[PDB]
Length: 172
Image 1 (cartoon, rainbow, N blue to C red):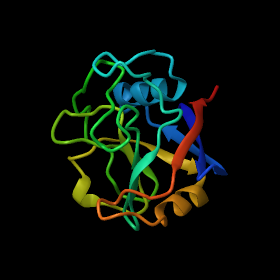
Image 2 (cartoon, helix red, strand yellow):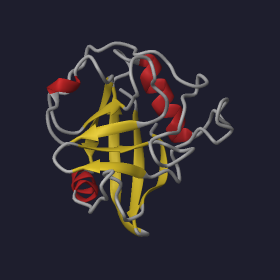
Image 3 (tube, helix red, strand yellow):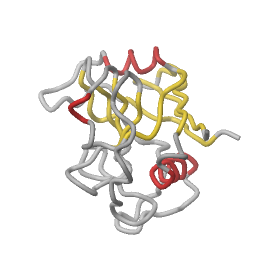
Image 4 (cartoon, rainbow, N blue to C red):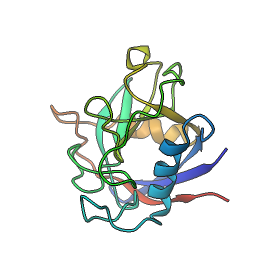
């Protein structure tokens, strides 16, 4: 099972590393996208012209007791990002359920609109089953997730503080 990490700073304070386990058996296309966004190895986005990489991206949507969301590397507000395939790719499958906290799952705007945005749940969310593709699990950095989850947000659930992926990468 491949692994990859984010190193997080909040307002430039280093707060720790989130380590992900990806389930590339069940969701190979989805995990390959997420992995390549961690290494940045695929270069410039085909529809966005921005680097296909999470490094320097933010968490732009936070809902306490629900989830934290990031990966919009082109707009930082939920409107952007795209996959390594060029624009969006199909919902690979909905085999894995949102049956626990700390799952990694694809953000979307309807069927088959997977790009680069992802979210991490902080509780079971079964109403999302068959809606968002689950492809991974956080296996370390729970305190980081907690910290991000408790940030003050505005009316659009956007954190006021800078929640920054300062580094990220694929593990051996």
